Structures are given as C-alpha cells and as structure tokens.
Image (cartoon, rainbow, N blue to C red):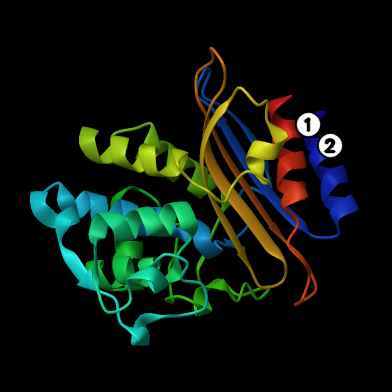
Amino acid sequence: ADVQQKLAELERQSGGRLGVALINTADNSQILYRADERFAMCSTSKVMAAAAVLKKSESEPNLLNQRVEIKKSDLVNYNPIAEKHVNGTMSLAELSAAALQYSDNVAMNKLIAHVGGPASVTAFARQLGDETFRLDRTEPTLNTAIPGDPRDTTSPRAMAQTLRNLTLGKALGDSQRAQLVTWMKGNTTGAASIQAGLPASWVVGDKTGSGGYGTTNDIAVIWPKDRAPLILVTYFTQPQPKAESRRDVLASAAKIVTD
C-alpha cells in the first residue's frame, strides 16, 4: 505494498521523479521507491565530505582544529557563514558544522579541497562499501542536476545504507560518529522537509539539498519516540529547469512511509 501505491500517487501528483529509501533498524526492513535510480545529491553530499574529514581526524587528532583562511576569492553562491569570516580563518570543525548546519558552500569547497578533491571524497565512499556515490564537481556546479547526468549523483538505496553506516554503524570512531550526529541534529535548514512529515516528538538529524530542475532532497537519521532509529532518504527532481523547490513533497513522502 500500500505504501508503494501511495508513493506512486504522490510522485504523479507532484509531476516529478521521487526516490525514497527507508531503513527501519528495528527489523532491518526497507521501504524502497526508485531506490536504485540516480538523483543529483546537491547539498546532501556535504555529509560525505564532512565524514571524510572526520575519518581523517581519527589518525590526525588535531585536524579539526586546523585553521583555513577564507578569502574573497573563496566566495561562491551561498556562503552564509563563510562570508562572516572573510580575511580570517575557520577551523575545519567550524567549516564542517557550517556545511552541515547551514549548507555553506564555501565550507563544502574547503572540506573537498582538504581531503583532495571530489575523487577523494568518492574514494572515501568506496572505502565504506558504497560503489554508487559519485562526487564529480565542486560547489557550485555540482548542483546543476541535469536529467540523465550521472555527475554528483547517488541512489536512495546507497545513500540510506551509507548514512546508516556513518551515523548508526561503525564507519567512524565513537567520537567522530557522535560529532557527525550532533552536527546533523543541529541542522537549521530541514524543518520544512522530512521533519515536517513526522510527529513533533521525533528527533531528526538531517541534511537537505536543492538544486537545478527543482531538485529537492533530504537525508535523515530519525529517532522516533521509544522506537529503534530509522534512516530516510527522500530525493525529488522535476522536469523543468526552473521548477521551484518542493519541500512539501519530501514531507509527504516521510509521512507516507512512517505512517
């Protein structure tokens, strides 16, 4: 399924292409909708960049305190935090939090550069057992989200499995996993997306993304009241280049799959 039918109806009503992966860790069950198709990740890829820096810090303890200069030349399209720090430095921890909690695109680029570019982020994903994830480009061009373009895409299934590994599994050390979960729980950008489709009492750590073709994304680790945690990936993209974002569609998907 009944849930499948409802997701299909939502997708049809919405006029776009919807990809959903829910992992219920209570019974290791999955709800999948277009879960093996590729979707542009947009800013949801920031989780993998931050995770790659956190993994690095397991062998370089002082790494998150390392200072990175922010210059005017670094500014891109959306720099809500970095623009306050031009001509100064931010720590890698501060950059990670900015990327994850405010979707700062300078912060993302600094994380990408630190670990050695998009192919290094991708190689990190491969190390985790994710052979689907691919980060090709830096900010801001990784958000073009052109249909049929595999650059900077992943599938809902792969991203849910990987997100499970990062936040609930052992991909990262204890301290690094906690830090990632803490950052994602402090996200400021997700209240209208998956969270808006869940009960108020549930706890969510998520990363949103949006981009060209009205791409509207959210990936979340969810702690329902008195239940085992869930992983939910909701990817949505639309046919028209200038389509508007549809965060409501992600909230609706979230409600359908958690009902």
Classify 10 Å Cα crowding around label 2: few (below 14), some (14-19), many (20 and above): some
- Mark drawn on residue 3: 1
How far across and how far down the image is residue 61, in percent? 10, 49
How far across and how far down the image is residue 194, in percent? 65, 41
What residue occupies the far bottom of the structure in this picture?
Answer: 73
Q: Quadrant of residue 121?
A: bottom left
Q: Is residue 137 left or right of residue 252?
A: left
Q: Amino acid at mark 2?
A: Lys
Q: How far apart, in angstroms, are the residues tagged by discs 1 and 2? A: 5 Å
- Mark drawn on residue 6: 2
Q: Is residue 108 left or right of residue 217?
A: left
Give the answer, above or below, for where 82 lies relative to 26. below
Q: Residue at x 51, y 56 (%)?
A: 44
Placement of the C terminus among the 4 image quadrants: top right
Q: Amino acid at mark 1?
A: Val
Q: Is residue 31 left or right of residue 127?
A: right
Can residue 48 be seen in the rendering of this structure?
Answer: no
Q: Residue at x 30, y 62 (%)?
A: 123
**Badge 1 vs badge 2, beta-carbon distance below 8 Å:** yes
Q: Residue at x 46, y 71 (%)?
A: 79
